[PDB]
């Protein structure tokens, strides 16, 4: 009656004892002392029986034996050669007699050692027992990463060094190695994973939502799980009532915010979001019950249920589960021989983004030109003078914020009009954008198109036309979005009314700053006729959307480091 | 719309927010300081938006958007470089569909998901038994005959009854698993396919499913048969002799890449919480595994990110290399 | 009649056994236990008459 | 029995900040995370974990 | 007198303190390995 804590000590003792000697005969075969230790412990651990006898089995001298030990002849010879000693060859046996039979004294007791295989179970059709076998299972980690910079420590500095300028050792592991039964090198690689993860069973999430909906779900804030519609306005009073709605509608801290938690604090038992993480492709959140997405601007009160959405970005998993050091090591793995920025252009770019005295005249020009080639085709001299004057007065480059501005600079104002330093900066930036697109291209395999989607769209996000740029100057991206998919059920919402009309070439008489219908200014075609019955044509190619999305989602946020902001203009006062 | 890179507040030559009003919808472009450009700005909105990004509900919720909070937190809290940060952002920007993950794995790209493989193995066992001296009282009866007619002659059936009694006070006889001898089952590499199993929900496009089964057929030793015989067990496609014995499956369980490695270095749980599969000797690099023969008694434990786990299996001093 | 796969296991067993002890007298000359192990295995592997 | 078990002392002398080999615990950072004073101590359990 | 056990102030020196290359590290920069001074010297396997 050793109560609970000593029972758990007994638990651990049985654990380490089963792990300790399960195959000890072939384990410590070169150490005969341990074999005798285990065998003598085995013999002197069984309680003896009633000592009832009239005539028993004794040796030739007369000392009675204490039992029989039965094994197979292989282990008989293995213990007989060097581990245990022979006591005698014959023995005394009753008849209801001198019989040759070996016997060994172990510790304090004397025992027969039998390997009865020759006399019986030989040349007969009964299987010999004691060959029952086992069923063992092995655990074998595959692709974990040493998340801490504490854990990226070596034995000696250049243990596994190379000749490259970057040692191919920063990278997270992708394969594991072990030994076969013959001792040859064996390999598991992540290419072996289609038999588990690349099946349709990854999206069997419905029954878990049904089971999880049966729990006690409490009322939390409806900010990050709720989608509204546009209210057909000038987008000013909309952020108005958004401001005095958002100013007090959170009763506490939203749960999808605290990415600053480490590994252990996230997996701590006190975490309420720890029980909300089931599937790596899914985010589980508390949602309004029987409220359609999108719901109205005023959130209706309902009993809160749980809903789940797809994790399209693999980085949508929390950074306690996907560390920043791991992502940086992965980016280092990608960028071994790819294009990089020379220190001159990178210091110019960081100096012109961390400039706070930036004039708004560039903003005015970008707003009025609004990404139209016809506007830029008539403003060569003004743009040349403005760019030159801003450049050789503080050594900061300008008009690099807008993506519909700088390839124009390279194509038109690139023959030598500008100073040579700026043109090399723009060429390096476009070279980096093209190198990022090439990095996307080389890591996907073409030739397989399913449901009309190219493999570029199937593999990556910045090459899919379903996902769009944060800011659209032209309507060509929307045309590619609702034309390229054709199986993705589309729904576009522009401030109330659904859909666009894309009416371009607006003039003095009908500028109509207070326009509330779905006329959107696509832009004047340069090499064509505007017209009225002419259907709207894209300004540029399919690669325009790819390059623009790559720019807005790589160059701007990584260099700005989450400091720049997107905002709308007030043309009714700007013009 | 437009983007301005830096916010200014003490520029009194131009009135604040007379040309722009802040309408930020992106986790990446969250602008807590630019919100003073909008009218009706107070201390409450600033102290509430310094921790929570301002995103309108009518332009996409954070849970419903493609770009979410973790990528924004990654880009706002990383200080390594700019080239490495941009390439890290590029490597983040990938789909997680089965077609996509197949693309990154057969390319060679490493997604942010860790794994384990589980391997059921069988071994021959020699058993060691010591019983006792006075353990059994064993009664014999008398032999009795039975003559029974047969096809050509007669059949004699001999019958002798008997009884056994264990006259032990407690546990007298103890057996123990002793030796290994020849392992009948293979310690190689065969991946466990799920495409055998049926009962889960199919996905919408059957050609995509057939293409996925075709891809899973490549790169494996056991695969489903190409005619797909319905009304049956779906036995695997045959071959000649597996080179050294019966192969064992390898079923995959996914973990985050942030996982305690020292947990797996002992006898651990396949689930991840005790409430035990023995890991063998293993390494994640070819160099450390060939080093792991104890060269200079060389225990290379971890070099940079690839790892070596010392053997926790019961087969410690067995299976020579 | 162990069919094909155990015949290939027997194949590899013969491979490693021929590679294992072809010249064991001069191989494990400094280890007297392996000599006695091989000799005792050899003498008790043939059936008598 | 009782054990003494030091926690957070520091190698105050600059002569005491010596290694076995120059890079034994080296990293990819420009600053080696080994200059710091210790904050935690390690030992073994009775089962050796 | 309290007998001090085997102890390390880094995870590296403890995990290499099984005498790897018979590796007796004492200090690397500031963290330390103290060899076992308890009577339980040749006991308690790792």
Image (tube, coloured by chain):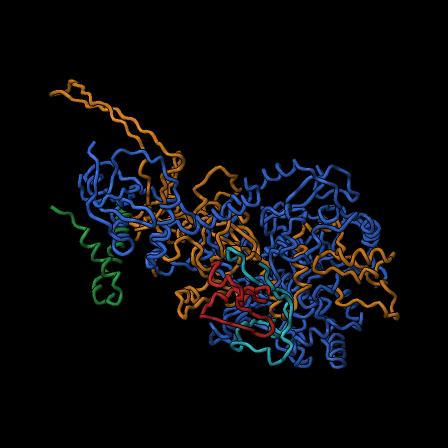
| Residue A476 visible at all | no
Image quadrant in which you'd find residue B226: top left
In the rendered view, tell whether residue A5 sits above or below residue A454: above
Q: Is residue A100 left or right of residue A244?
A: left
In the rendered view, tell whether residue A552 sits above or below residue D21: above
Chain drawn in red: E
The shade of chain D is cyan
Image quadrant in which you'd find residue B145: top left
- Please tell me which residue lies in front, A441 or B177: B177
Chain drawn in blue: A
Relative image position of residue A15 (x, y in whole percent):
48, 48
The shade of chain C is green
| Residue A168 visible at all | yes
Chain drawn in orange: B
- Please tell me which residue lies in front, B149 or C2: B149
Q: How many marks?
A: 0
Residue drawn at the location 86% of the way across and 64% of the way down: B16
Q: Is residue A309 left or right of residue A201?
A: right
Image quadrant in which you'd find residue A208: top right
């Amino acid at each position: 009656h050793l109560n609970r804590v000593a029972r758990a000590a007994l638990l651990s003792d049985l654990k380490r004892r089963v792990c300790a000697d399960m195959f000890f005969m072939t384990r410590h075969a070169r150490e005969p002392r341990l074999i005798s230790a285990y065998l003598s412990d085995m013999v002197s651990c069984t309680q003896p029986s009633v000592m009832v006898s009239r005539i028993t089995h004794t040796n030739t001298r007369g000392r009675q034996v204490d039992g029989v030990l039965v094994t197979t002849a292989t282990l008989k010879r293995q213990l007989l050669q060097g581990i245990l000693q022979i006591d005698d060859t014959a023995a005394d046996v009753p008849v209801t007699a001198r019989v040759p039979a070996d016997l060994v004294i172990v510790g304090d007791k004397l025992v027969f050692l039998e390997a009865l295989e020759r006399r019986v179970y030989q040349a007969t059709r009964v299987a010999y027992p004691l060959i029952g076998n086992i069923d063992i299972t092995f655990i074998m980690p595959m692709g974990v990463f040493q998340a801490n910079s504490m854990d990226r420590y070596t034995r000696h500095a250049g243990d596994f060094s190379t000749v490259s300028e970057q040692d191919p050792r920063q990278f997270p592991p992708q394969g594991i190695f072990f030994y076969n039964k013959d001792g040859i090198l064996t390999q598991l690689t992540l290419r072996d994973a289609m038999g588990t993860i690349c099946h349709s069973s990854l999206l069997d999430v419905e029954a878990t939502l049904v089971a999880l909906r049966q729990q006690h779900l409490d009322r939390q804030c409806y900010f990050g799980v709720y989608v509204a519609e546009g209210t057909e306005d000038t987008l000013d009073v909309q952020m108005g009532r958004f401001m005095e709605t958002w100013a007090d509608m959170m009763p506490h801290h939203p749960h999808w915010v605290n990415e600053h938690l480490t590994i252990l604090q996230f997996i701590a038992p006190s975490n309420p979001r720890l029980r909300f993480e089931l599937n790596p492709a899914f985010d589980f959140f508390v949602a309004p019950g029987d409220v359609d997405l999108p719901g109205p601007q005023r959130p209706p009160e309902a009993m809160p249920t749980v809903n789940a959405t797809l994790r399209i970005i693999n980085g949508n998993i929390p950074v306690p589960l996907c560390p920043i050091s791991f992502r940086d090591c992965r980016g280092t793995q990608l960028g071994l021989g790819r294009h990089t920025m020379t220190p001159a252009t990178i210091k110019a770019v960081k100096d012109t983004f961390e400039d706070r005295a930036y004039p708004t005249i560039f903003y005015m020009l970008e707003a009025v030109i609004h990404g139209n080639e016809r506007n830029f085709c008539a403003l060569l001299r003004l743009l040349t003078q403005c760019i030159r004057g801003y450049w050789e007065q503080s050594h900061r480059v300008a008009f690099v914020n807008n993506f519909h501005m700088l390839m124009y600079i390279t194509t038109y104002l690139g023959n030598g009009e500008l100073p040579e330093v700026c043109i090399n900066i723009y060429r390096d930036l476009l070279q980096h954008v093209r190198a990022l697109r090439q990095t996307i291209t080389d890591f996907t395999i073409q030739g397989e198109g399913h449901n009309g989607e190219t493999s570029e769209a199937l593999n990556n996000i910045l090459t899919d036309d379903t996902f769009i740029a944060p800011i659209l100057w032209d309507c060509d991206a929307l045309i590619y979005r609702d034309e390229a998919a054709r199986d993705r059920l589309p729904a576009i919402r522009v401030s109330g009314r659904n859909g666009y009309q894309a009416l371009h070439f607006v003039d003095m008489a009908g500028h109509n700053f207070q326009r509330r219908d779905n006329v959107l200014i696509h832009g004047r075609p340069v090499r064509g006729d505007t017209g009225q019955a002419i259907p709207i044509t894209p300004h540029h190619d399919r690669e325009w959307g790819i390059l623009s999305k790559i720019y807005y989602y790589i160059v701007i946020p990584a260099f700005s480091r989450g400091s720049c902001c997107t905002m709308g203009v007030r043309y009714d006062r700007l013009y | 719309g437009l983007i301005m890179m830096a916010y200014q507040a003490y520029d009194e030559t131009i009135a604040t927010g007379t040309f722009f009003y802040p309408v930020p919808v992106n986790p990446l472009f969250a602008c807590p300081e630019h919100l003073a450009s909008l009218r009706g700005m107070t201390n409450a909105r600033r102290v509430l938006a310094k921790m929570v990004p301002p995103i309108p509900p009518f332009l996409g919720a954070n849970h419903h958007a493609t770009i979410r909070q973790p990528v924004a937190y990654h880009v706002t809290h990383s200080k390594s470089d700019f080239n490495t940060l941009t390439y890290s952002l590029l490597g983040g920007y990938f789909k997680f569909t089965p077609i996509s993950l197949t693309h990154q794995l057969r390319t060679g790209f490493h997604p942010g998901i860790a794994f384990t493989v589980v391997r059921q193995d069988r071994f021959a066992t020699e058993q060691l038994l010591y019983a006792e001296r006075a353990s059994e009282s064993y009664f014999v009866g008398q032999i009795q005959v039975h003559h029974h007619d047969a096809i050509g002659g007669v059949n004699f059936t001999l019958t002798q009854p008997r009884a056994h009694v264990d006259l032990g006070v407690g546990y007298t006889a103890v057996c123990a698993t002793a030796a290994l001898r020849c392992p009948l089952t293979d310690m190689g590499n065969t991946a466990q396919n799920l495409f055998f199993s049926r009962g889960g929900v199919p996905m919408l496009h059957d050609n995509v499913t057939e293409s996925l089964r075709r891809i899973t057929a490549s790169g494996g030793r056991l695969n489903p048969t190409e005619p797909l015989p319905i009304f049956g067990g779906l036995r695997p496609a045959t071959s000649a002799g597996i080179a050294r014995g019966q192969a064992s499956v390898c079923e995959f369980v996914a973990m985050p890449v942030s996982t305690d490695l020292q947990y797996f270095r002992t006898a651990c749980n396949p689930r991840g919480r005790a409430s035990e599969a023995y890991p063998p000797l293993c390494s994640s690099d070819a160099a450390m595994l060939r080093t792991a023969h104890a060269g200079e008694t060389g225990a290379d434990e971890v070099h940079l990110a690839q790892y070596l786990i010392r053997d926790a299996s019961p087969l410690r001093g067995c299976l020579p290399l």
